[PDB]
């Protein structure tokens, strides 16, 4: 990825990543994080 | 699906599902809505 400016452009960062075997387990943890973090905030929103 | 009491399960209903042809895509939509629903209730929390 790079920081694009008005008619000049320069390098920001890069990762030589290495993928993994579990598309599902990854997506599960992402969804579970959201649904938990959602729910805790609606509890706080009631209390406040 | 079923409800359990009197130490046994009791069917409440049934569905014909169909396996979905575009799996990763409806998953995309779902995690977008969840990331929104975090951010929305988080914004309400800060205000409260």
Image (cartoon, coloured by chain):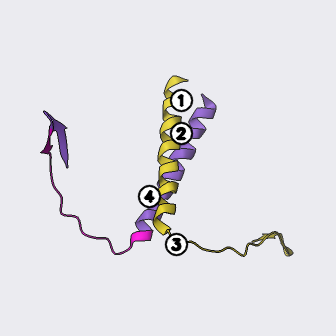
Chain colours: A yellow, B purple
How many other residues sit within 10 Å of disc 2, few (<14), some (14-19) or many (≥20)?
many
State which chain disc 4 sits on.
Answer: B
User: In terms of secondary structure, what is the magenta stretch mainly?
Assistant: loop
Which quarter of the figure has residue A16?
bottom right
Same chain shared by disc 3 and disc 4 = no
Q: Viewer-nearest of labels 2 and 1?
A: 1
Same chain shared by disc 2 and disc 3 = no
Give the extent of the magenta segment: B8-24
How many other residues sit within 10 Å of disc 1, few (<14), some (14-19) or many (≥20)?
some
How many other residues sit within 10 Å of disc 3, few (<14), some (14-19) or many (≥20)?
few
Query: In this figure, which residue is indicated by the disc labeled 1?
Result: A44
Residue B30 marker: 4
State which chain disc 1 sits on.
Answer: A
Residue B41 marker: 2
Classify residue A6 as left or right of residue B22.
right
In the image shown, does B40 or B12 lie closer to the viewer?
Answer: B12
Q: Secondary structure at mark 2?
A: helix
Instruction: Report the number of discs.
Output: 4
Asked whether disc 2 touches disc 3, contact meaning CB atoms under 8 Å apart, the reply is no
State which chain disc 2 sits on.
Answer: B
- Distance, label 2 to label 3, CA atoms, is 33 Å
- Distance, label 3 to label 1, CA atoms, is 37 Å
Tell me which residue sits at (51%, 49%) in the image. A34
Asked whether disc 4 touches disc 1, contact meaning CB atoms under 8 Å apart, the reply is no
| N-terminal-most mark, 4 or 2 | 4
Q: Position of residue B11 (x, y in %)?
A: 13, 47
Tell me which residue sits at (15%, 36%) in the image. B7
Q: Is residue B45 magenta?
A: no
């Amino acid at each position: 990825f790079e920081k694009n400016l008005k008619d000049v452009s320069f390098r920001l960062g890069s990762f030589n990543l290495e993928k993994v075997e579990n598309p599902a387990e990854v997506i599960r943890e992402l969804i579970c994080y959201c649904l938990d973090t959602i729910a805790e905030n609606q509890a706080k929103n009631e209390h406040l």
